[PDB]
Image (cartoon, rainbow, N blue to C red):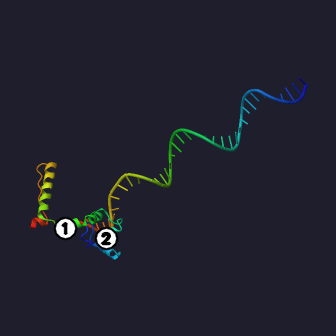
Amino acid sequence: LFTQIFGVGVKTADRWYREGLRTLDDLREQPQKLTQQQKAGLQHHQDLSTPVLRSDVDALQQVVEEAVGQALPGATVTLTGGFRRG
DNA sequence: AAACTATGCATGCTCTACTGCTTCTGATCTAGTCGACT
């Protein structure tokens, strides 16, 4: 549960576990020991927990292609990662 | 002719300011460690 939080690794998860933090809500009760990454991940937890689909990939690729084309002409963008493996 | 007072000088103590040299402190910066991510 803790590792899925953006900006939370194994070390931080273990540190929280040994400190008595057991539930997600408990993390929100003390919003003073979390960096920007952890706060951003915890706030948009539900949104980031959902696996992404291919339509969202296409929309994001179109948006980024438009942005790079307007920024610098002739830019080429290639989709890598898991989505390139099928 | 004698006493009082105006004038001045010499010196020590004190406030006040100003200039310059030296030292201390606040501010501007690279190495080590842990952690995040990919």
The image shows residue A9 at horizontal and vertical percentages of: 27, 70
For residue A53, which quarter of the picture? bottom left
The image shows residue A73 at horizontal and vertical percentages of: 12, 48
Position of the C terminus of chain A by quadrant: bottom left
Write the residue at 11% across / 63% down.
A54
Q: Nearer the viewer, residue A19 or A42?
A: A42
For residue A33, which quarter of the picture? bottom left
Chain name for mark 2: A
The residue lying furthest to the left in this view is A86
| Kind of residue indicated by mark 1 | Thr
Write the residue at 30% across / 64% down.
A39
Look at the picture and state if B7 lies above or below B37.
above
Q: Nearer the viewer, residue A52 or B1?
A: A52
Circles 1 and 2 on the same chain: yes
Q: Which residue matches tag 1?
A: A50
Write the residue at 22% across / 65% down.
A47
What element does badge 1 sit on?
Answer: loop
Chain name for mark 1: A
A56 with respect to B14 (left or right): left
Q: Nearer the viewer, residue B31 or A51?
A: A51
Q: What is the spatial separation of the Cα atoms under label 1 and label 2, in whole angstroms?
A: 19 Å
| Kind of residue indicated by mark 2 | Asp
- In this view of the protein, can residue A79 be seen by the observer? no
Kindly indicate whether the residue at mark 2 contacts the one at mark 1 (C-beta within 8 angstroms): no
Write the residue at 30% across / 62% down.
A36
Residue A72 - label: none
The image shows residue A35 at horizontal and vertical percentages of: 32, 63
Q: Which residue matches tag 2?
A: A25
For residue A15, which quarter of the picture? bottom left
Q: Nearer the viewer, residue B8 or A51?
A: A51
What element does badge 2 sit on?
Answer: helix
